[PDB]
Image (cartoon, rainbow, N blue to C red):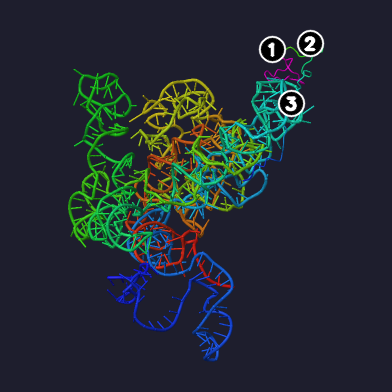
Amino acid sequence: KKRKKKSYTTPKKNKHKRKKVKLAVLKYYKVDENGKISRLRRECPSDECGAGVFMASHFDRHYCGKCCLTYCFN
RNA sequence: CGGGAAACCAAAGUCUUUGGGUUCCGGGGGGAGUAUGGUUGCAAAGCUGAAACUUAAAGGAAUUGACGGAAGGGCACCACCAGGAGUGGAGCCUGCGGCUUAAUUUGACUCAACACGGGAAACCUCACCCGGCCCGGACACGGACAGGAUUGACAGAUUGAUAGCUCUUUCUCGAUUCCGUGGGUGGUGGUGCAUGGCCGUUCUUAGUUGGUGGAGCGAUUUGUCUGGUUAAUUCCGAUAACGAACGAGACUCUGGCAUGCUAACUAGUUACGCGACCAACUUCUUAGAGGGACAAGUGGCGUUCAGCCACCCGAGAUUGAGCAAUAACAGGUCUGUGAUGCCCUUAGAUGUCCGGGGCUGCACGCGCGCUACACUGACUGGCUCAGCGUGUGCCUACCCUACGCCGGCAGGCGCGGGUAACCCGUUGAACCCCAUUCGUGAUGGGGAUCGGGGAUUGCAAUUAUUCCCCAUGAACGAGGAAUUCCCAGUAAGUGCGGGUCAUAAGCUUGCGUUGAUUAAGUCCCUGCCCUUUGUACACACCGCCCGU
């Protein structure tokens, strides 16, 4: 009988903290400075979500989790 | 009388009611009858004879127990036996220590540990484990609000892993929470040397205890015993004991027996019955108010008592088990239980998630296990065979099973029955037998691996699940030292069913089937009990104790 001796890797770990900025700079912008503005996200043609569901942007396969939708030309 | 602590003593009496005369002599135990001085002796040694120091007892009598390589009498296959049978070595892997790093992993140190925790380890139960994350505070004090992170992406990877952990997106319940110390909603966290309750054992034997009365100053003893008898502290009897109380017996369950009884459309049936001249008042099975066996009859042994032996008769003539006395043990269990008293670690909570190394090695460190020697062992498939039992929703998603795809049958799919004496099933890949056979024993006779036919369908099985055939030839016919169990439906062979479970068994708990050589004795070994005796033991012989 010995101990588990789980020490050889990762003696201490730091909590991950996402630096989610409180200001609307990276997520959205207007680039117009007017009452009417242009939206920087493609319209979602699916009816399985709400009328204000706006998709985020990655390198590909825009990840939202609810749909896992990917733009494909079939 | 009397006296003594008593053992005992007519003296060890005439003693606190103390004085007949007189001599020697002791003052806790050791040091020590030692040192020294004197004295005697040829010598060995004799006589007289300290102290320093050391110690809380040493010692006497007796009482109970324990022990005895002490006696007497009994008893037990956890004992033995010119007795044996089967053994641990010849056919189905597990438990824990010896025993390389992720491998020898908690509790249990002879009987009273070691398929034991009903503990059959991938994993939820793995703490030896190559690796982590979602993390805890009714409060004592600290860091301060529309952000101070939650299991939650294949393709550049991870250390196996469709786990965002990649030094990665600034997707996503959204005020949920987090760090430093513990009480806490607790921890299968410690301590079973704090406990309860359950067990196990001393201890399977017959043992044990008041009341009142006797004995003793008393601890204590008698009762509870010289004998005979019994399996028995069972009885007869004896008797300073008499009356009692437990334990033993009785008792309960279970087997074994009815030209008897109570009755069954699930076993069982009678001449105005057919499908055949060419609505039995219940008995085999099932189960009930009863019966039956009492050493009852006879013979012989026994202060002619208790009882013992034998024999008819009888289904059966010490007949399976269960339950089981206070004191006991620092026996096991805190890991069965918001059954339960607090000294006290860590974030790598002994929580989850078909996820994941071992232990399924072979110079064995041990223990429980898996196995029959010949016309008896097994095939012709040529006659009606057994059980004991189990079987489908609070939880819950998991039950037992009756035809065909067809190679040759469980069976990958359709199919009905059974909450059960209704179905499985008069228990669906089974006797031990036999026109495949041994002529005197390595052949046909019982299998060393290990390969194919469709695999029950369990991710994995190999780091435990899953059939018989080609006859490929293994010391191929009573076994180191040490030994374990056992006396009639014992043993042993053999299969089957329950528990565990997913029909998971080499384990255990039960059940039938074939069927039994030896013994109706003993105290030799190991122990136990009813006495007497000894003890310088009482932590009780694993004791105590002596020696430079």
- Between B229 and B300, the residue placed more toward the observer is B229
On screen, residue B173 versus residue B69, left or right, reads right
Most common secondary structure along the magenta stretch:
loop
Looking at the image, is mark 3 or mark 2 earlier in the sequence? 3
Write down the region rendered in magenta. A52-74
Residue B443, image x, y percentages: 50, 47
Q: Residue at x 63, y 45 (%)?
A: A2
Q: Is residue A20 magenta?
A: no
Badge 1 vs badge 3, beta-carbon distance below 8 Å: no
Identity, as a three-letter code, of the amino acid under mark 3: Arg
| Badge 2 density bin: few <14, some 14–19, many ≥20, Cα 10 Å | few
Instruction: Determine which residue is flagged by label 3.
Output: A18
- Between B117 and B65, the residue placed more toward the observer is B65
On screen, residue B1 versus residue B107, left or right, reads left
What separation in Å lies between label 2 and label 1 (alpha carbons)? 21 Å
Residue B240, image x, y percentages: 26, 60
Both on one chain, marks 1 and 3?
Answer: yes
Q: Nearer the viewer, mark 1 or mark 3?
A: 3
Instruction: Determine which residue is flagged by label 2.
Output: A38
Q: Could you tell me which chain the residue with mark 3 belongs to?
A: A
Residue B483, image x, y percentages: 46, 56
- Looking at the rendering, which quadrant does residue B359 occupy? top right
Q: Could you tell me which chain the residue with mark 1 belongs to?
A: A
Residue B373, image x, y percentages: 45, 50
